[PDB]
Amino acid sequence: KAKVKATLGEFDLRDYRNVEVLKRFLSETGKILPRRRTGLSAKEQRILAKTIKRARILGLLPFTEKLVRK
Amino acid sequence: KRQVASGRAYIHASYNNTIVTITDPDGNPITWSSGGVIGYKGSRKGTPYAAQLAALDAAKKAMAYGMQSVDVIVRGTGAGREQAIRALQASGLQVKSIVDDTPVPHNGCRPKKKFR
Amino acid sequence: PITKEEKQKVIQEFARFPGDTGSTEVQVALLTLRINRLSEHLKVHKKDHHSHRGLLMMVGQRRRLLRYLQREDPERYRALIEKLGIR
Amino acid sequence: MRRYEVNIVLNPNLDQSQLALEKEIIQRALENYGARVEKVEELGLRRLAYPIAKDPQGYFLWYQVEMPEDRVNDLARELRIRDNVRRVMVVKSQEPFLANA
RNA sequence: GUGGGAGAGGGUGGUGGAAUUCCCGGAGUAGCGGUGAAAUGCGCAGAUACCGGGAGGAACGCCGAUGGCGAAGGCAGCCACCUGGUCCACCCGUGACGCUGAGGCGCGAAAGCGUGGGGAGCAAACCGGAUUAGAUACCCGGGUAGUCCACGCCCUAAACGAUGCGCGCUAGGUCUCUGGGUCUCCUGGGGGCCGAAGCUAACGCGUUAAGCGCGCCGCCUGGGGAGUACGGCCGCAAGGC
Ligand SMILES: [Mg+2]
Ligand SMILES: [Mg+2]
Ligand SMILES: [Mg+2]
Ligand SMILES: [Mg+2]
Ligand SMILES: [Mg+2]
Ligand SMILES: [Mg+2]
Ligand SMILES: [Mg+2]
Ligand SMILES: [Mg+2]
Ligand SMILES: [Mg+2]
Ligand SMILES: [Mg+2]
Ligand SMILES: [Mg+2]
Ligand SMILES: [Mg+2]
Ligand SMILES: [Mg+2]
Ligand SMILES: [Mg+2]
Ligand SMILES: [Mg+2]
Ligand SMILES: [Mg+2]
Ligand SMILES: [Mg+2]
Ligand SMILES: [Mg+2]
Ligand SMILES: [Mg+2]
Ligand SMILES: [Mg+2]
Ligand SMILES: [Mg+2]
Ligand SMILES: [Mg+2]
Ligand SMILES: [Mg+2]
Ligand SMILES: [Mg+2]
Ligand SMILES: [Mg+2]
Ligand SMILES: [Mg+2]
Ligand SMILES: [Mg+2]
Ligand SMILES: [Mg+2]
Ligand SMILES: [Mg+2]
Ligand SMILES: [Mg+2]
Ligand SMILES: [Mg+2]
Ligand SMILES: [Mg+2]
Ligand SMILES: [Mg+2]
Ligand SMILES: [Mg+2]
Ligand SMILES: [Mg+2]
Ligand SMILES: [Mg+2]
Ligand SMILES: [Mg+2]
Ligand SMILES: [Mg+2]
Ligand SMILES: [Mg+2]
Ligand SMILES: [Mg+2]
Ligand SMILES: [Mg+2]
Ligand SMILES: [Mg+2]
Ligand SMILES: [Mg+2]
Ligand SMILES: [Mg+2]
């Protein structure tokens, strides 16, 4: 299982209104994925965070979800 | 006296004790059980075995109401919450699904000295 | 903030010859603009201390250029003082 | 005057008259606060991630604007006054930082 | 000066979700809680567990780092406004305008003080419970000041890199944050780890010196007595220098 960045086109890292993309940086739970998974860079990740959070405020993205099985 | 037959089973398990509650699909209780509900009194209520028996009790009391299938919601980390799962599966109640709901704060409240 | 036209109009105003950006006159002027604004923002926001340190620093810088300019050409000093409203 | 994006999320259960009224009152808000409008993107019904005002969904508007500096905050206030407007987020515009490029 | 950046740097206002407590309603019984084991405690005036609704205060999970910013103390949800510092490129302007700094003035964690507010969780003092030679203590149940906000004081600390500031000079290697470039890489600014020469009582330091040098400030001169006494200055007090 490789990085999220690895499979995707050129995408605005700043767009909080685009869920079809941003969804892919969250885990099963609402959590924002670690760099190891996101495949982003320092600056990159740092921007993605803010973007996601903005989106969550708007209710387009989960603050948290519930874990299935386990 | 109800006739539910499909519903929700919540397992709330702490290090001290394990309690099970079986409810109707919109969340209202049907029956419940726990370590103290069966024999045990002290620390004995936290053992995996007590969890087993509490799950089993709850399931018996459920199949009296007519419960057939159940969606499981697990909350907490405790000795044999997984035992309450394992018990609740072989109970004869067919389990539809299992979810871990353990509530977690986004860091609101100062915890007790034993928790820092 | 201080936008570009705002700043420029000040440099135009205080430049010795055309094109002069960094002379003593202009440095003092620009500095002074910054100081004034900062003092306005510290009239309310009395609790913003870090900005205030900034003020002390700018104030000091200005006094340095002034002491110099006055040392080298007292006339230009009195001129600059009169124009700006300092001391 | 700077460049902003006004995000308005309002209640999905509105019919014509209602929607057009909230929308026109928003228009009036911007006109009163000196906010010129450039682009307007109305996305409408979307399924929210968590229920907002007990509603499973929301209705979305996105405006791009240019407005004076000190008036933005007060603008947001007079937007949120409306009972049927659930959430407002006004955001300074930014250039499109890309990635995987 | 111009053109670019990155940033929990600061101030103000607004807003978002998780959680805890409490209140309301439903459904539901016999316990819950808690420990090494227990008891106090709460539960039949219906608790715990579960669902819906409301109120309030405080703090911001993931991102998060061995990361970033700040002179230090210190700074972490999101948004807007007000604002400080700083890095780079271009080589455009001024023309030694520099460094340091006794005194002064300002900032200064936590606790603490004054006058108002606020008070969910935590909790000095205190009130209880079991441990068990013994409880003023480690464990358990409560709980007040305080913790939070405004304004005004206090001025301490392992306020630590236990390393004053500035400049020049003296091998490299490696990881990293942030710019620029003709982006096998090179170049500038930060953060780390190994190491040349050198230094060091040793441990260690080693282009982020504890090396080689210059400038300026602070400070030291065996232990105990003692950061005590006396005096002075500051403080409402505690108490500080
Ligand atoms: Mg127990
Ligand atoms: Mg079965
Ligand atoms: Mg307590
Ligand atoms: Mg610039
Ligand atoms: Mg900040
Ligand atoms: Mg702030
Ligand atoms: Mg109730
Ligand atoms: Mg009893
Ligand atoms: Mg009783
Ligand atoms: Mg509630
Ligand atoms: Mg209350
Ligand atoms: Mg972490
Ligand atoms: Mg750090
Ligand atoms: Mg520190
Ligand atoms: Mg700035
Ligand atoms: Mg030149
Ligand atoms: Mg010349
Ligand atoms: Mg002296
Ligand atoms: Mg001094
Ligand atoms: Mg203090
Ligand atoms: Mg304090
Ligand atoms: Mg007292
Ligand atoms: Mg007080
Ligand atoms: Mg009081
Ligand atoms: Mg005793
Ligand atoms: Mg206690
Ligand atoms: Mg230290
Ligand atoms: Mg020295
Ligand atoms: Mg290095
Ligand atoms: Mg580089
Ligand atoms: Mg590059
Ligand atoms: Mg380096
Ligand atoms: Mg070494
Ligand atoms: Mg050697
Ligand atoms: Mg030496
Ligand atoms: Mg040696
Ligand atoms: Mg050695
Ligand atoms: Mg040196
Ligand atoms: Mg030495
Ligand atoms: Mg002596
Ligand atoms: Mg003393
Ligand atoms: Mg005395
Ligand atoms: Mg006196
Ligand atoms: Mg003392």
Image (cartoon, grey):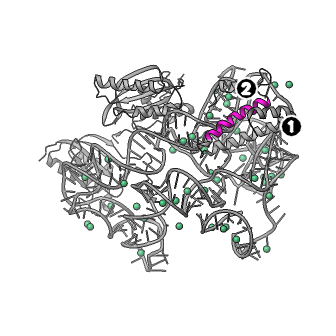
Task: Give the magenta part as a residue range.
Answer: C16-41
**Quadrant including the N terminus of chain A:** top left
Q: Quadrant of ligand 44?
A: bottom right
**For residue C11, which numbered disc appears in the image?**
2
Q: Which residue is mark 1?
A: C71
Per the picture, the main secondary structure of the magenta-coloured stretch is helix
A36 vs E138: above or below? above
> Crowding near pointer 1: few (<14 within 10 Å), some, many (20+)?
few
Q: Position of residue E27 (x, y in %)?
A: 18, 49
Secondary element at image label 1: helix
Chain to which mark 2 belongs: C
Give residue E151's position: percent from left, percent from top: 56, 52
Instruction: In this rendered view, identify the residue nearer to me: E151 or E123.
Output: E151
Q: CA distance from mark 2 to mark 1?
A: 23 Å
Say if the magenta span includes residue C28.
Answer: yes
In the rendered structure, the answer to whether residue B9 lies left or right of residue E79 reads left
Residue D64: mark: none
Residue D10 among magenta residues: no
Is residue A38 among what the camera can see? no
Q: Amino acid at mark 1?
A: Arg
Q: Could you say whether the residue bearing mark 2 is in a helix, strand or loop?
A: helix
On the question of residue D77 being in view, the answer is yes
Instruction: Give B62 or D36, whichever is nearer the viewer.
Output: D36
Q: Nearer the viewer, residue E201 or C21?
A: C21
Graded by Cα atoms within 10 Å as few (under 14), some (14 to 19) or many (20 or more), the crowding at tag 2 reads many
Q: Amino acid under label 2?
A: Ile
Rendered location of residue A45, percent (x, y): 52, 33
Q: Residue at x 86, y 35 (%)?
A: C74
